[PDB]
Every structure is written in structure tokens, then in C-alpha cells.
Image (tube, rainbow, N blue to C red; front, side, top):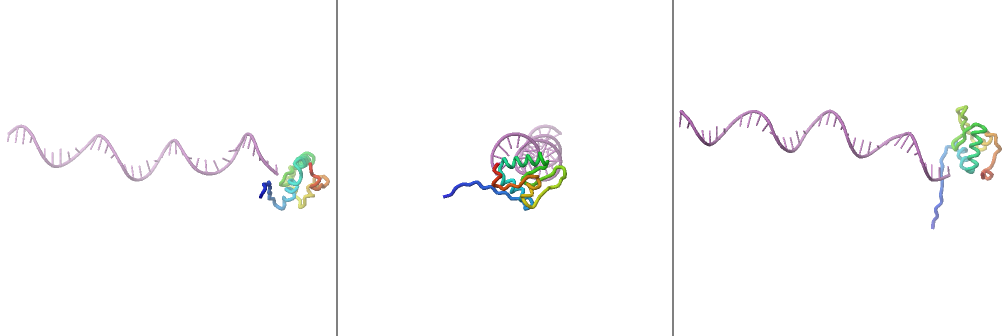
Length: 84
DNA sequence: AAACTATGCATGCTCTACTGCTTCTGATCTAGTCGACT
């Protein structure tokens, strides 16, 4: 016998790997809140591809996912604690 | 010598193909709107 299970596949470059990983691990509400905080408080645009500064037209990529929280002035969280 | 017949020719008409130019039509590429998803 067999069963039908939904599977989602995403391909991203190594440079953008942490950004996509963060975008997909966190909950929908958590991602929305993080994006709103980034754009309103820190004034930076956050999406699944990278972090952008409208003032200085240069990407703020980083080699580790924790750098995203580090540069946004937020304490680091693990995926288990990002449940909305 | 005159009447009838014969050939001969020309021109307008009809059709079928042939070629080239012009216009219409069918196939192929994108903006917007709604919807689906992560």
C-alpha cells in the first residue's frame, strides 16, 4: 500500500542559505512579526532571499543564521521556541 | 457578263494559366487581475 504526503522543495544559494532557512523554520506569525519589526524598528527589509538596507544600497548577508538575529538587535532563539 | 460559292483574314470574346503586388487573417509573445501555494 501507499499514502499521499505533501512535500515542498526549495533551492537557494549558499550565500542566501541562512536567510531561506530562517524564513522556512519560523512560524507564519513569527515570520510576519519579524519582518514587521525589521522594517519598522530597524528600517531594514527582510525576506526569504536576504536583508536589505534602503538607505545604503548594499546587502547585509552573513555566513550564519544567528547573525540575522545578532544584527537586528534581538536575542537569539532556537527553532523550537519560534512557535508563534 | 452576272450570280453564287470559296477561301482568307481580321477583331472582339472567353478561358486557363502564369507572375507580381496589396490587404486580410491566424499563430505567437506579455500586463493585469484573480486565485493557488509556501
